Image 1: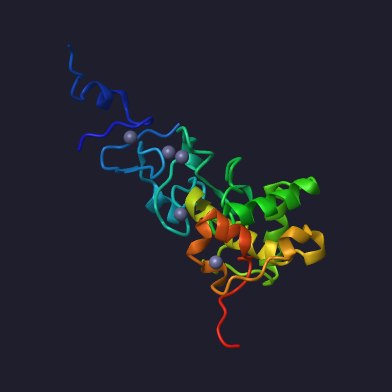
Image 2: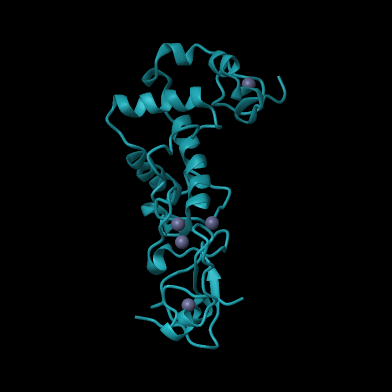
Length: 213
Ligand SMILES: [Zn+2]
Ligand SMILES: [Zn+2]
Ligand SMILES: [Zn+2]
Ligand SMILES: [Zn+2]
Ligand SMILES: [Zn+2]
């Protein structure tokens, strides 16, 4: 496929098929990759970067897909900045929506907790990343740190796990009594019924699956 990117040489540009009517410069032997976020081609400089840390990262270190954001700035409605060190990743203004088990009732309790104290999702992440680094909190992508360079999606995923543990560590006396009165759901955090408003309001889902007595 003929590909022309922001950094392709002018002679390549003019040689493409015309439309229908009613510092770096890509070399000839070089290849392009499509940014996973915006689908725009960029020069594929990953191999070069393996022996040259001066080249900007072009992939998520968790999922290993390519992203253009650190390389030359990505732009798309919906993209907040799709590749960044975890501690600097922009998760967007609505990152707390359904942040707990995709459960808006549990999420809103948390939002209230934070709003009450003037805390932002940012302060909460910062505090969580401290616990993570000491081994107090854990991640499924267990080797991720605040310094890991990753994508919006992989960062969001670990942010949900960290946020869950943050919520878990809030004392029951710091939450409305309307919250702490609710009985634990037998099925705990992975309950499938909690996407229904009535069940979600009635039972607490910040807990683990009930096994024996
Ligand atoms: Zn190019
Ligand atoms: Zn990723
Ligand atoms: Zn992009
Ligand atoms: Zn992007
Ligand atoms: Zn339930």
